[PDB]
């Protein structure tokens, strides 16, 4: 069925137990990305996580989410056939731009928030919002940002919270997760705050090479807007970051709310248009740091 319906070509990239190869639908020649999961040695419990991801991805159909077209089961191998995206990471793209302002960062965050809101409307919490999962659909200057990798996503029932587990990437983890408290949709809005922060200045709000002091920072909500770099950032941008980086997740801004924040919905009159070279230079260093993997910026095993 799989080799009758698709033809696998080169490897695009990988995961901690999955390869992604470009593929073409037979006989139409249409391209997709196939995520290939070797299932021969998987536990039932691990296969159930694959079942969850396939199920969640089949539900989600949105301009800013990489669409799953097909979930094929064969003997020892499962295939998740996704839309192909050729623009790479949003964050790598930003560093190659000649001109980058708050209005650009707003444009990005707006798309990210539309995808998060669609997830949340459909009872899905992503739990690992991070630059790695934010890909441009194509290399076009106009390309949509698309949300990827639902390998850690959970299905919530309405606005009921639960102890879904300690899962995610340290630098982007929310206080309630770290606290071993019940959680839900708000954890994705904390993660967006962190991403927005890094989108404006190019370094993370919570940073310490000692994982323990990293978590104490997060739980205390101890981030600031230091000079000179934040001095040129609009009050409205900081206000949004503040509303997302609220320790009490009940009082944290929702995705829908964040889409009506003036910095987002009134971008053209509220977001600063000044080039932020120093951000592009910092993002360069940030991205380079991320490439090295290790403790803070890498999804927890
Ligand atoms: N899911 C998941 C994780 C994942 C793993 C590898 C990955 N790399 C990657 N992915 C892609 N493209 C891609 C990935 C997907 C689908 C989101 C898995 N659709 N398109 C390309 C395309 C061209 C050059 C290089 C590429 N690299 C992107 C995402
Ligand atoms: Cl479809």
Image (tube, rainbow, N blue to C red):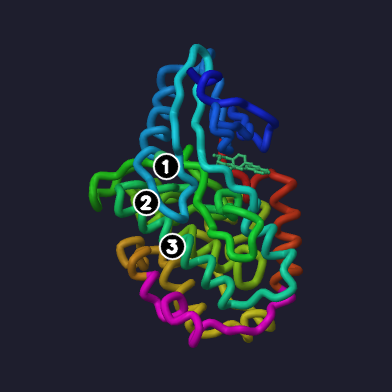
Residue that numbered label 1 is attached to: 153
> Which residue is found at the position 43% from the left and 62% from the top?
113
- Give the Cα separation between the discs numbered 2 and 1: 10 Å
Residue 168: percent from the left, percent from the top?
50, 45
Helix, strand or loop status at disc 3: helix
| Residue 34 picture quarter | top right
| Place of residue 178 in the rendered image (x, y in percent of width and height, measured from the top left) | 45, 50
Q: Nearer the viewer, residue 148 or 68?
A: 68
Question: Can you identify the residue that label 3 sits on?
Answer: 113
Q: Are marks 1 and 3 in contact (CB under 8 Å)?
A: no
For the C terminus, give its image quadrant: top right
Question: How many numbered discs sit on the rendered protein?
Answer: 3
The mark that comes first in sequence, 2 or 1, is 2
Give ligand 1's quarter of the image: top right
What range of the chain is rendered magenta?
Answer: 258-278
119 vs 74, left or right, is left
Alpha-carbon neighbours of circle 3 within 10 Å: few (<14), some, or many (≥20)?
many
- Whether residue 288 is visible here, answered yes or no, is yes
Q: Are marks 2 and 1 in contact (CB under 8 Å)?
A: yes
Residue 156, image x, y percentages: 29, 44
Looking at the picture, does residue 107 appear above or below residue 249? below
Mark 2 burial class by Cα count in 10 Å: few <14, some 14-19, many 20+:
many
The answer to which of marks 1 and 3 sits earlier in the sequence is 3
Q: Is mark 2 within 8 Å of ligand 1?
A: no
Q: Is residue 273 magenta?
A: yes
Q: Quadrant of residue 260?
A: bottom left
Res 119 label: 2
* Distance from Cα at disc 1 to Cα at disc 3: 16 Å
Q: Is residue 197 above or below residue 23?
A: below
Q: Is mark 3 within 8 Å of ligand 1?
A: no
Q: Residue at x 72, y 48 (%)?
A: 291
């Amino acid at each position: 069925s799989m080799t009758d319906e698709y033809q696998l070509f080169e490897e695009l990239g990988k995961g901690a137990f999955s390869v992604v190869r470009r593929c073409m639908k037979i006989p139409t020649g249409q391209e997709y990305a196939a995520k290939i999961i070797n299932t021969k040695k998987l536990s039932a419990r691990d296969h159930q996580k694959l079942e969850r991801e396939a199920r969640i991805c089949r539900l989600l159909k949105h301009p800013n989410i990489v669409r799953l077209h097909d979930s094929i089961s064969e003997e020892g191998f499962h295939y998740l056939v996704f839309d192909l995206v050729t623009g790479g990471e949003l964050f790598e793209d930003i560093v190659a731009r000649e001109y980058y302002s708050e209005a650009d960062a707003s444009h990005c965050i707006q798309q990210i928030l539309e995808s998060v809101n669609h997830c949340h409307l459909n009872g899905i919490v992503h739990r690992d919002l991070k630059p790695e999962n934010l890909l441009l659909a194509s290399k076009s200057k106009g390309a949509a940002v698309k949300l990827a990798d639902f390998g850690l996503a959970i299905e919530v029932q309405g606005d009921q919270q639960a102890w879904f587990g300690f899962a995610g990437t340290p630098g982007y983890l929310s206080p309630e997760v770290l606290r071993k408290d019940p959680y839900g949709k708000p954890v994705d809005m904390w993660a967006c705050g962190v991403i927005l922060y890094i989108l404006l200045v190019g370094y993370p709000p919570f940073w310490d090479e000692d994982q323990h002091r990293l978590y104490q920072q997060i739980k205390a909500g101890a981030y600031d807007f230091p000079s000179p770099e934040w001095d040129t950032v609009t009050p409205e941008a900081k206000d949004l970051i503040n509303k997302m980086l609220t320790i009490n997740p009940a009082k944290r801004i929702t995705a829908s709310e964040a889409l009506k924040h003036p910095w987002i919905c009134q971008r053209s009159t509220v977001a600063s248009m000044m080039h932020r070279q120093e951000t592009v230079d910092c993002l360069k260093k940030f991205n380079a740091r991320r490439k090295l993997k290790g403790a803070i910026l890498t999804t927890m095993l």
